[PDB]
Image (cartoon, rainbow, N blue to C red):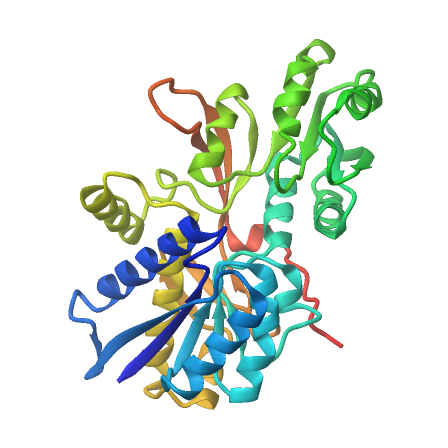
Length: 371
């Protein structure tokens, strides 16, 4: 009777992540309902739809969920390109789509509509949290990014947040997306910082292969008194960070950082069931579960207009503590975590030790959905 559709890239390149989203969603619904899978008398049923991270298949799966399966609400999807394609389907069917995990800023910006909410963090939250984490008086930063919208828009968001922190931005380098040799750009970055007083940091934003952090580290930035910094990542990706002891940045999640009853249960039970800790996608799927149950409980209905009214400005509890759907753009505001890398040779990933929890009010996330 409460029918939730999960759209996810169960097969294809994002398979591993999609499976984690599903695990988090089911564990979150279990937690929220004390294992009953019922809410105010309604049995909760989850319908999963594999979109193969293909946008045309995603649009069709979501329509099918709303129209054939009678889903009351949907959560999706793994690929930002698929999620962006899906947004008009929510509007056409007058049903809510809770976006999770897709991060693309445009989902709550230029391409947003009133039926779209998002529990996943957006790419602006990633960049901004990094600026707030590392930006202080006595710090000078140079940035390295790929020459494409993700890189440029990420550095733009970082730069705007950094301006209020007391840190100075010395230079911005943008290199072809396919760059694998960082010798030339590395030297420009080092030359831009080496004579500055105080602390000097190269902050990197990068998607895909190329391994700029390792390649810059191989050039020995410490000889110029320069530190490297980048955002956090999923556990398999953190293996590479074992080469960067003491590196700081900000992350969406690391299992051992948040200390709250929800995360405590999630971590303990996930380890018991699967012999591994929860990751980004697990935490986000859980957050989406909690958003749905809190909304339906508050609305006392699955009517879409009642759900929108209930969800705008709505606080809900997650493994990351409190999240709130901002009324204007329906983006979940949420904590982010300033970390410092610790290298434990017995652990497969670099350990992200807590420096500070960046609370919701510590980050100004721009509102970009005004047309």
